[PDB]
Image (cartoon, rainbow over all chains, first blue to last red; front, side, top):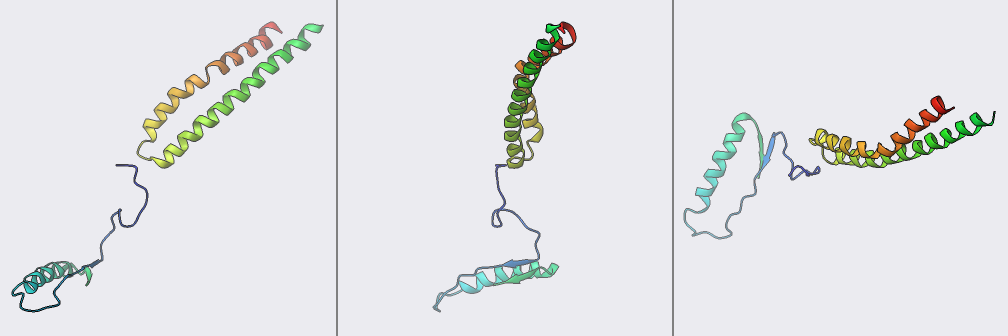
Length: 57
Length: 77
């Protein structure tokens, strides 16, 4: 649509700082669940941090 | 003589009331264009086309009243 009004969440923005919500376990013994998620997060987090884009968790 | 007294006044009422209807009709029709230009930019040239189509029909009967008040003034009196 072209009928869009102004509204932060809907409209884009030039990027300097990015936030991640990470869900993770209260409990162990789940095996290689958490760490195979967290290395993917850190790879992406490193990718932005490569160009100096800030990040938050 | 008595002729020009009344025939100016008759043209005056003709072009005076035409001056009401064309100004009020293009005021209402134009303000609805300008909320549409504010509400939908990117469409100004498309809406402007529609505004000029509709404006030619609003000016129809008021332009016959102007043209005959110009006739009464500079032809009949």
